[PDB]
Image (cartoon, rainbow, N blue to C red; front, top):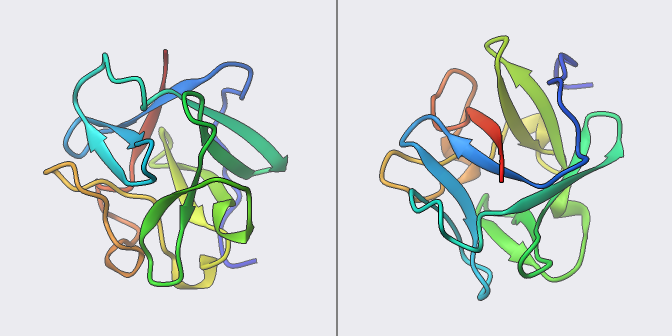
Length: 141
């Protein structure tokens, strides 16, 4: 395919917080579908349940609202009420430590899930291997 296959350890048995080491924000999918990051651990919209659709391919869903993380045709993350092709991400190990999520739909363009230091999501085309914005650590809820 277009990418390596080093996979992170850990599993999907329990929900997780997706912590971005760039600004220290947790990925958040709000009830209205907007996606961004927050440093508030008490937020009820940062609890995410991941599930494997195929080895290395995942859905990332808000446990609070049931919404799926998805990246649209112009690279913007949004919350989807139903699972579709834009909701699948290739979950990979990075720097022998972190988890990265590449849009399956746009994998050939290397579009990643990423959070900027200010907590706003990065648009797909603005992401790339090597950035801290794409590095996540799944933490217990």
